Structure formats: structure tokens, C-alpha cells
Image (cartoon, chains in turn cyan, orange, blue):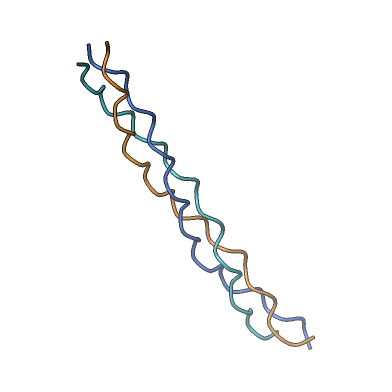
Length: 29
Length: 30
Length: 30
């Protein structure tokens, strides 16, 4: 005997992603 | 006796996208 | 009696990288 318990709680949200890559070169002076 | 532990919970959601990258380098010249 | 609850689901994947940064500032005066 013995029935399986309830499904566990859902996991936490993943960590925020890393910053995007550096931007492109700026305009000429 | 009591049954076995339940199944693992649903996997968490993907994280938020990261922030914008740093500004680009200065334009020419040297 | 029913069994204990299953373990918590695993944490989700990490977010993707953010957008590329903006354009850099103007170059130095000639």
C-alpha cells in the first residue's frame, strides 16, 4: 500500500541574463 | 505505510533577458 | 496514507544576453 504524494512545488525562475555586448563605434569627431 | 514521495515539481521558467550592453567606443580619430 | 510531496523543481535556465549597447560618443576633435 501507500499512494505517491503530491507533485513538488515548481522551481524558481532562472537568473537574469548577462548584459548585452558592447555597442558599435561612435560617430567621427 | 505512507506512500513514496511525490514526483519532482515542474522546472522553473527561464530568467529575464539581461540589460543592454555598454555603449560602444568613441568614434574616430585617435 | 499518501506519500510526502516531491522535491521542488529545479531552477530555470538563465536568461539570454541583453541587446547590444548603444553607439559610442563622437570621436575627439581634429
